Image (cartoon, rainbow, N blue to C red):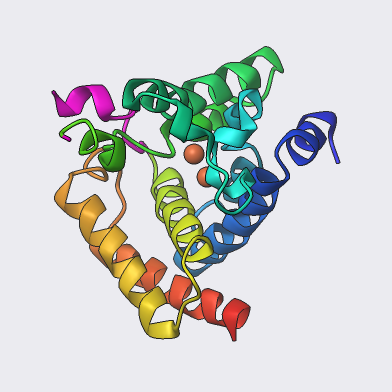
Amino acid sequence: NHPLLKKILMKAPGTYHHSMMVANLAEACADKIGANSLLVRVGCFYHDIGKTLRPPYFVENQLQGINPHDRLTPEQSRDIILSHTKDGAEILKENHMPQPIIDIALQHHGTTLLKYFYFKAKEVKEADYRYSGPKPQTKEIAIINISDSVEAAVRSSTEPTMAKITEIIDGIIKDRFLDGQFTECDITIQEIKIIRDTLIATLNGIYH
Ligand SMILES: [Fe+3]
Ligand SMILES: [Fe+3]
């Protein structure tokens, strides 16, 4: 591995394994709709590199029942999570990575709402609990957004049927559609359907 990629494996082995899995999912979707597969693959490898700044605050790096967000305000939690896109982009820039890889790290959550920490701060304005974006500017980044959300949800679920996995994927796509996250790229509804069906198929080769 390249020094940059190995620093992900060493500091945040969960994030690493997660990123490899996303790359697999997302590249398969890129194939099926004839998007830029190789940009998608390598973009996923680095998309979460901003988590290397504070690895234990991301669940894929945590041990069961040991969550550092307990000793934190929602605000503190939000500031750490919302930062990792911007921080990843900055790390990538400082390492003179190609701009499309930089764009992916910055945009892969679009402007989505951190809803958990948003409605824990009920028990205040949405804009403060949303990623800075921009929203995905390309089909490729939209694919990654969906794949990334799907990977993490299935990973953290215990432990899912094909029916559950389908439900998770449809929920996320619905969410993205209703929240307008894909209105600044050219991804088609037909492509969304292909992506959706490819994720179901790939994930079942993985969960049997
Ligand atoms: Fe991320
Ligand atoms: Fe991710």
In this picture, which residue range is highlighted in magenta? 123-137
Front-most of residues 65 and 49: 65
The correct choice, above or below, for 34 with respect to 63 in the image is below
Residue 125 located within the stretch drawn in magenta: yes
The correct choice, above or below, for 109 with respect to 71 in the image is below
Q: Position of residue 197 (x, y in %)?
A: 40, 76
Q: Position of residue 122 (x, y in %)?
A: 15, 33
Quadrant into which the N terminus falls = top right
Q: In the rendered view, does 164 fall on the left or right side of 123?
A: right
Q: Residue at x 44, y 60 (%)?
A: 153
Within the image, what quadrant is residue 123 found in? top left
The correct choice, above or below, for 31 with respect to 37 in the image is below
The correct choice, above or below, for 79 with respect to 167 in the image is above
Q: Residue at x 24, y 63 (%)?
A: 189
Q: Position of residue 90 (x, y in %)?
A: 57, 16
Q: Residue at x 47, y 65 (%)?
A: 154
Q: Position of residue 89 (x, y in %)?
A: 55, 22
